Amino acid sequence: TTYGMCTEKFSFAKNPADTGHGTVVLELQYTGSDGPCKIPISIVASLSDLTPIGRMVTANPYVASSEANAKVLVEMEPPFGDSYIVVGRGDKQINHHWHKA
Amino acid sequence: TTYGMCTEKFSFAKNPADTGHGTVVLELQYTGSDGPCKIPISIVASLSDLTPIGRMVTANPYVASSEANAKVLVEMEPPFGDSYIVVGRGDKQINHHWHKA
Image 1: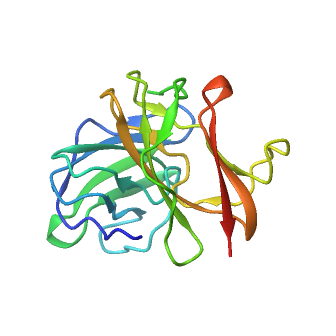
Image 2: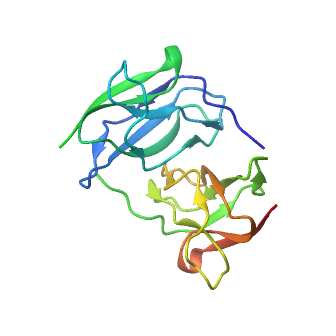
């Protein structure tokens, strides 16, 4: 029993939100109807240095349903300073710049 | 921006499923209507030795919606041998015995 990587585009349902203890909560929606599937998500230093950095608090999250616009709540621990949240893959990829103080 | 721990009972929507590479996929449903909330989930050696062991592949998962019977897909890496998946808390807790070979 396995599921594939999600192939369709995600969207940020709300702003990434500072939790107050160095982590960030993000409510995503998945515009695919093809789930359950594994979410391609990482934190990167820049859009050219795509080595994953930081830590996913909600590691390896899945879209759990085939419902349209399925909601997934992810939490991450970016490094201090500037980083990008990158969700989705390829032409479907979206990104969001985060500054952690 | 924070969410609480889920307080209501979960159910196993399907059997825990061997992925073929030492991990287990579980499709849960949350009977609460009070989400988003953080799922109390761990792997334990016995129902008396409740020290969390193993590894959560999908670490720190959330119920992402207030919909009834929200689906969440979790993956875990139990230790070899016998362990229990325990989901939910207190009187709401459910458990499932797993044997990893």
